[PDB]
Image (tube, coloured by chain):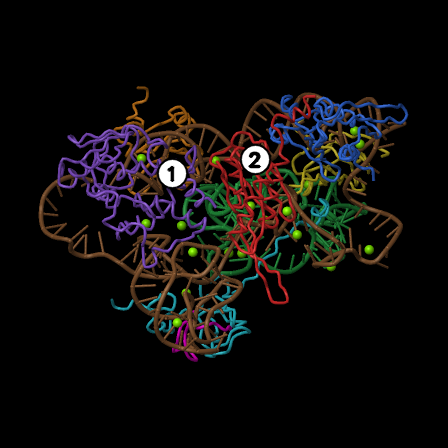
Chain colours: A orange, B blue, C yellow, D red, E cyan, F purple, G green, H brown
Amino acid sequence: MVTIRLARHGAKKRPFYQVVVADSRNARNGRFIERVGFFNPIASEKEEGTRLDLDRIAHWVGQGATISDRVAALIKEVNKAA
Amino acid sequence: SMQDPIADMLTRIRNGQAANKAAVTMPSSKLKVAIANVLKEEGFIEDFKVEGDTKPELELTLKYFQGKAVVESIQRVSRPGLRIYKRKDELPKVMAGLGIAVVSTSKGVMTDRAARQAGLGGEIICYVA
Amino acid sequence: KIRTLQGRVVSDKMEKSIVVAIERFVKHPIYGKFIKRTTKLHVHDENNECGIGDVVEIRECRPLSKTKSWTLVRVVEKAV
Amino acid sequence: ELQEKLIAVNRVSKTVKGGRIFSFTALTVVGDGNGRVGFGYGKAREVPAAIQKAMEKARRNMINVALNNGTLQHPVKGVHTGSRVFMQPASEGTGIIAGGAMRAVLEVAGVHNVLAKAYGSTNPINVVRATIDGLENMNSPEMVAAKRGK
Amino acid sequence: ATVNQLVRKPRARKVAKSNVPALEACPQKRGVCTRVYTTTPKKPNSALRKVCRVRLTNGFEVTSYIGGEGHNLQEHSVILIRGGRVKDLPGVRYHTVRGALDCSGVKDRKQARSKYGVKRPKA
Amino acid sequence: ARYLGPKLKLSRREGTDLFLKSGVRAIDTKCKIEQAPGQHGARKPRLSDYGVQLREKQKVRRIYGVLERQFRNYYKEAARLKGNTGENLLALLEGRLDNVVYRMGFGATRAEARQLVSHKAIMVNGRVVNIASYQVSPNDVVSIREKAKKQSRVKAALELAEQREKPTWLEVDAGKMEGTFKRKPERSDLSADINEHLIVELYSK
RNA sequence: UAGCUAGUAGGUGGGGUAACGGCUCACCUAGGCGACGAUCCCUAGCUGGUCUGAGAGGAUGACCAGCCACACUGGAACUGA
RNA sequence: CCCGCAGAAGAAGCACCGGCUAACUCCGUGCCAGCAGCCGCGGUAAUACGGAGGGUGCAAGCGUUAAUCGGAAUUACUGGGCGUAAAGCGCACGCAGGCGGUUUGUUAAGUCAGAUGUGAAAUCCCCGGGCUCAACCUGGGAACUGCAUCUGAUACUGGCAA
Ligand SMILES: [Mg+2]
Ligand SMILES: [Mg+2]
Ligand SMILES: [Mg+2]
Ligand SMILES: [Mg+2]
Ligand SMILES: [Mg+2]
Ligand SMILES: [Mg+2]
Ligand SMILES: [Mg+2]
Ligand SMILES: [Mg+2]
Ligand SMILES: [Mg+2]
Ligand SMILES: [Mg+2]
Ligand SMILES: [Mg+2]
Ligand SMILES: [Mg+2]
Ligand SMILES: [Mg+2]
Ligand SMILES: [Mg+2]
Ligand SMILES: [Mg+2]
Ligand SMILES: [Mg+2]
Ligand SMILES: [Mg+2]
Ligand SMILES: [Mg+2]
Ligand SMILES: [Mg+2]
């Protein structure tokens, strides 16, 4: 089943995830279908750190896909609208 | 053996010029004409002339400015052995702009200045500066 | 249609095993000169009719025989 | 704004009954900085004599070339004896990059921002010379109109 | 010349022989001393140059130069050899890495000690 | 990393003052500048175009106390950055904290001014920056840390800092011992006696 | 290395496969490929790209990603989406 | 990452200096010992051997070797040559192949135009943002100079016809 998950393209001790749709059986940082956000867990208070193309995501979710524990978490944190 | 007429033009010119010769003749053809035009229009020669019906005959009047001739260099660029075709964005500009390149497009035989404006491409016949 | 080629026959002499030539012209990717790159194709024609030297129109179908993935669509000229 | 510089100084041999008699040769280039450049050769039994006897030759023997502000108008090729030289306008960033020996003529000439390379022999006496005639044959970024317009 | 010609038979780039079959591009190879010679050099020069023939780990048997002044190197000595001809000894195309395996460093060298494998003498 | 040897020896060979003993005295002497960088130092080096090309960049290098590696990169950068390679070189070269430290007069020599940096006793827009090559930029503000403020060296330092031409693109204080990098130094600031397009030519072939 | 090719190339019918198919078979046709390089020999995983070069090019295919292939060597299937 | 503590305290080496190539003297040696990327240094004043003092270049690396491209326009498409330097088959005929005077019509494959899809991400590059800087990490563009379908244009090339 196709899933949305955190591919991790960080850097030793400074992780930075590419959130991505893909064939669940593929390598973490491997073949995906499309990128649908990113999540910088260092981001910091400054500005950006969790851009998330909600439109596509919840279209794949409807399309059939499913979501990581740690991705859905970013969504009921991003709030959704405001 | 007369397998490239356009080269023979380019050269009947080139030579006749270097031989400070006022006139120049040759058998004609629509293609010769369309070029003689551009050569006159862009002003590398005084004026042309085709005298005959059965066996037409281009005639070109060579310009000379100071002691020199006006045509500093006339060179084939496409040819039977090896043909050339640049698009529009890839058309050549001779002498950085000065002088010009004859090019046949689907909308007639123009210069690069022209074709660029026309927005299209063709077979770059020759260069002339 | 969805695309289609032409090209002269070259061989009719086999029970619907028609073969068609397809000459092109292409820039030599290194020396500019345009040269002739031919393509032969094993095309199906039922009730054998296309003849050696006939120009003919051709379309691409599913695999008929090992070797055949094209059928004819029309004919064009004969008696070369 | 005198501006001058020698490019290559060399030794040569004559050979006579008594042995080899040596001598030297300088090749130089003087330019005003705004077009106008000439080269002089000149040779003499000793070096200073020859490098000076050269500088002068250049002061005479001086062409002038139609610049276009800091640069050439179009690209040009030059070709004397075994040297085939090529140099190009180059919408300056820095420029003046070229085969030291034709960098010589190019800077005194006043071009400020060109790229060049020398093909064939880099025989100085023929490059600085091939380039001169090069710049020379170059032509009026306007008075091609002279030729034409008409 | 012709475009046809070039089309028929394309231009081909002269491939480069090495000058040092230290087989497959190898920084150096190990070998055993078949002979410890000292022959004399060519035309202008005149000397008694120390060399040796070495059977290499890889089969090749080749003469290599022993740099420096003096060396305990004999038949059966296990040495290392690197590129580097010696124009004077025609047919000598390799040098022996003084200070490697069983090759001593030049004694008492103070200058350029890293070539001629010599350790920093105690200050 | 840091040169570390005799400082004047350099100025002598490079033929000019490099302000490496920058401190008290002026217009050297009390040294011997010129006529003997070594045993044959007197002899005139009728030196090649490569020679001069080499020494100019070497001069600029002995000046800011930078090694080939970094310097080569500075060039690499300048070249990338739009507009005249040779100038950007100098720009970059000046944006160096340690330099902006000495320039603001917190250190006699560029070296001293650098040791200052290395010893977390300096602060860009607030926080400590203990690395010499930190790039300073418009509006940035460097200041000596209270911890070791008005201490021996830096007094004298800020002192003969006015003995010097005193910059322009920046604004010292001397009380709060802070200073503001107003603008990227223009070409026309500094130099004259340094000839970029040589050290350009050098790294250009 | 200049000729290669009997399931070979095609047709018809049965069989077959998740599927089109000489995939298999039986019969019929005598075809099919090739100097635009077949066949044979030698070398080789391909790509995104990498290094170089002003470019055009040249060289290259570690590390990252994609595809393929292999799992002691040769062969076979079983289970199962 | 922050704070205090002690003492400059624990922390410089490698190649080179005849020319190309930045850096020169003495002593030892004497076609020996030896150097050597190329040229070439060594037979009594050796800046070229070896040591020394000096100097230049690098610097936690420095040199040597190996290796690809570069400069090499030295396989030349861009971008070369063949009288005497490497290079015109001893000569002719001619199949294939390449190229082919001139005019009109038609064709629209080459050629040209536009539209659309596609050209994975990373990488490269441009402007940014994040690690004290930097390497590194990262947002967004740009670029992927290619391919394919459709529609056009018809001067030039190809086909066709006379
Ligand atoms: Mg004369
Ligand atoms: Mg370092
Ligand atoms: Mg069947
Ligand atoms: Mg293999
Ligand atoms: Mg090049
Ligand atoms: Mg791995
Ligand atoms: Mg098996
Ligand atoms: Mg099964
Ligand atoms: Mg020198
Ligand atoms: Mg040595
Ligand atoms: Mg002596
Ligand atoms: Mg090349
Ligand atoms: Mg040649
Ligand atoms: Mg000959
Ligand atoms: Mg003959
Ligand atoms: Mg014609
Ligand atoms: Mg991409
Ligand atoms: Mg930053
Ligand atoms: Mg036609």
Q: Relative to G45, is B104 on the left or the right?
A: right
Foreground residue, F76 or F101? F101
> Where's residue B122, x and y in %?
68, 28
Q: Main secondary structure of the magenta part?
A: loop
Mark 2 vs mark 1: same chain?
A: no
The verdict on residue B34 being magenta is: no
Q: CA distance from mark 2 to mark 1?
A: 33 Å
Residue D84 visible, this angle: yes
In the image, what residue type sits under mark 1?
Leu
Pointer 2: what residue?
D36
Q: Which stretch appears magenta?
A: E61-80
Image quarter where the C terminus of chain C lies is top right
With D106 as the anchor, is D83 left or right in this view? right
Name above or below for residue C22 compared with residue H83: above
Q: Amino acid at mark 2?
A: Arg
Which residue is located at x 36 percent, y 44 percent?
A: F71
Query: For the point 43% across and 32% down, which residue is it?
Result: F83
Q: Is residue E112 visible?
A: no
Secondary structure at numbered mark 2? loop
The residue under label 1 is F89
Q: Quadrant of ligand 9?
A: bottom left
Chain of the residue that carries numbered disc 2 in the rendered image: D
Does the magenta portion include E73? yes
Q: Quadrant of residue A78?
A: top left
Residue E12 screen position, x and y as percent: 64, 52
User: Which quarter of the figure is the N terminus of chain C placed in?
Assistant: top right
Kindly indicate the quadrant of the structure image that contains residue F151: top left
